[PDB]
Length: 271
Ligand SMILES: [Mg+2]
Ligand SMILES: [Mg+2]
Ligand SMILES: [Mg+2]
Ligand SMILES: [Mn+2]
Ligand SMILES: [Mn+2]
Image 1 (tube, rainbow, N blue to C red):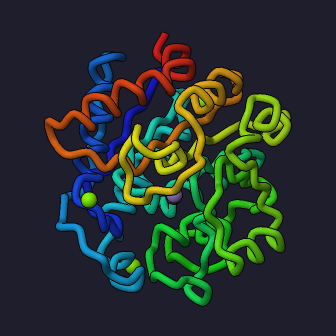
Image 2 (cartoon, helix red, strand yellow; image 1 turned 90 degrees about the vertical axis):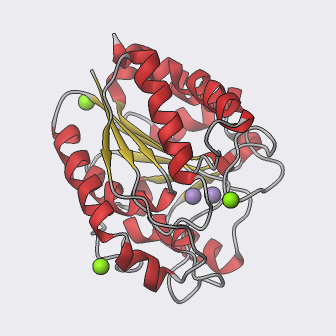
């Protein structure tokens, strides 16, 4: 009753071990739940390139992830995507919004990812993912997510340009100190639910990502979200931005903590 899809192609990766982090996460899920993952994309080298170069390069991987996501979301299994980068959600979020136009997206992240090409100060595609899914700019991978149905959980590092786009579009923001069961249940109400996680939401030290931003959520708060959302309401889960080298302490300890955070959802789905 779980479908596991794993991105292994470069999607604007600036960090060296996002593909390895995704692989280690997927292999641990495979072992815990006796799943066989659908691995898509071919690894390319990381680089600090503009979105205008990285997005074109990522098309093949994004289209293969979209195709596998569409097949699983049309079906009766919990859709689980283990994505190297948050940018893969440029492909998955338009699918979820087309299949489930009633769905609320819990976008669990330390940042807003709501810059456009006009507002971005870094040219990092990652900073433009949720705005892209919401059609504030054209990613070439579709849009159709209503910002009124997107909830930023745990965001604490939002540019004033980005904050303006977020308020006007009607994206709700739950800061990390308010990100409890009550606040998340108030946000999703009675809607079906898609969870999109960027591990940079977590208080630094624990689960390595690309970005390090203080005063974040704790692993138990993420576990509380998975415990709080009813199994009948959960469409699927996306896990992104584990930057963990092959065979490392950060790999084995991060993946133990991830297994613990997602167990309330995956144990229910796996039965
Ligand atoms: Mg790195
Ligand atoms: Mg293209
Ligand atoms: Mg279902
Ligand atoms: Mn982030
Ligand atoms: Mn992100």
